[PDB]
Amino acid sequence: SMSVKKPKRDDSKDLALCSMILTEMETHEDAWPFLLPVNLKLVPGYKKVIKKPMDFSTIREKLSSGQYPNLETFALDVRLVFDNCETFNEDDSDIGRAGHNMRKYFEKKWTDTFK
Image (cartoon, rainbow, N blue to C red; front, side, top):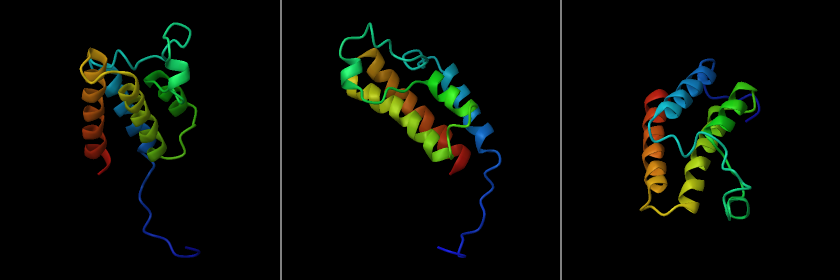
């Protein structure tokens, strides 16, 4: 509250560390469904159904342009990529499995870097 603060966590490396994690996600072999924005002209249903599209290239652009106020907003966008994937894809499909694998990969990197 006013004039009552928890001890100051050092957040000066967060930007660099989020960038590294994003690089690691981008270079994973199962990243291919998530690297670029879904083509809303060519994928039936996607525009209507997925209210907030998100992808790794868009996260990169946001990150590099100071559009994440903190590391939780970054994590929220990454999770949005996978939540979208689950909404639109059967679990039993290549893309469905890709999204599960990537989400796990991310959550491990996140816990190991910050938790």
